[PDB]
Image (cartoon, rainbow over all chains, first blue to last red; front, side, top):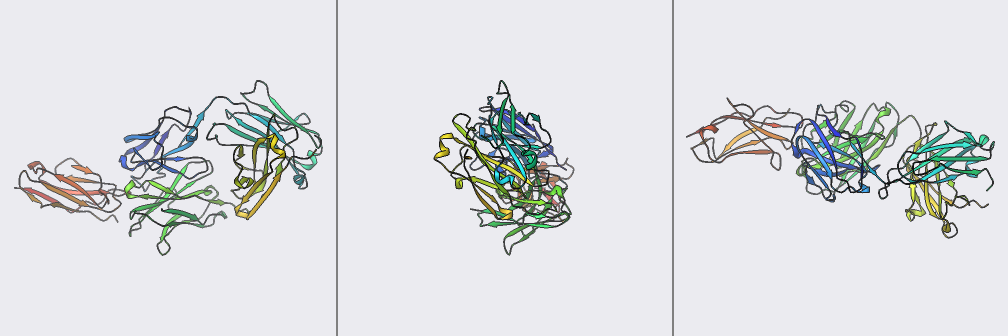
Length: 218
Length: 225
Length: 94
């Protein structure tokens, strides 16, 4: 076949940096059949470069590509927070007996100054208790880096196996993350205790932050 | 301008068959172009399925994986491209795109469709339940306050959550869906607001789950204590 | 199938010394690139990118010399592979 290899898979670069992505081919291809694609999370792909060096319509000037034969590059001369995306090279030279015309992808993450999270807590609504389930949400808002430690506690009892975390994508302006830990209990166990605590540990916090609410009362 | 519109996606049982459509709305000068089918599995990379050439030969090319199971055809009577998917397995669940590459761009895909989701599961559509994430009278971490909506127990993806009919965008964070132990989806949509606004502004989260025609408008208000 | 290319020269296949001859090769609209193969010469004698449209390619010789004399055969590369060679084109000099 023809394997298109990209490098690196992941990279962390700061705003204003000059990043360079590489795309290798298992055999020489004509440069005119080599293109670059950007894919912001959840969006459709987008054409950046074609013929390995030609900027496409509506593509910012800070993008450029070069290369010939087996090795190609894509360069971002002044990296921007919105350039957080995954980048694919693709070839239109040889199809047939080919697994993928695309490379593996290059995920570009924006490095940033540290930001402590703002922690919140949400008790179950009376509407959800009527269903017999209790969902308790803890919100970590606008933090960097992505690594955080969220531990649930119910009447000082450390919980495990009953919570799930969702993490946002890097924000296209301040390059921060937001995290939600949702604690799912039955209405039985929820009415079996009084204090529900969310203890958050982060790099930006000198000491952990604990958010707790006493059940029913304020 | 040219436009690529996709359809045919949705839920389908393992071992079944499905057909996506790509209707090319309008046209400009191309006269020589390919139509590609590309899919993206959850969190995985872009996968090229195959192309079809616009000429009378209607040459069709396929990936190594896709030969035999997938078939690309054309209906000029409606100017629609088809992707016939057979013997579907769970690992075939992905968002599917069709793209156009003109000869003048040396076959580079400048035009891309929105993408349609094909979920391969022996499970049924379920609409979500929407619950408020009420801001506690103490939750105001100083001058900022958080509130949101809990969109729980839906299937399949996706849901779209707007705030105040699209008028509240700053400070909104809608998290990716996480699959629960029950095979159903759940996500929260939150927004940070000035504590002073809890007596001036009304906060209504607008949830839309197209697969189930569900459309909920939950008003989030501070729980009166 | 990969229909085989049509290979011809202009103004003609017999060209005096010092004059211009243009060897034309015609493929399909999906041609990726073209090459020109000459007998008793290490392959390929020349390879060229397609035109727009990709139907035909152009090999030009501005001043015909005795080096350019012989039999040429043109191939074109489809997205799948190279094609069966064209019918031979002999280039006689006078």
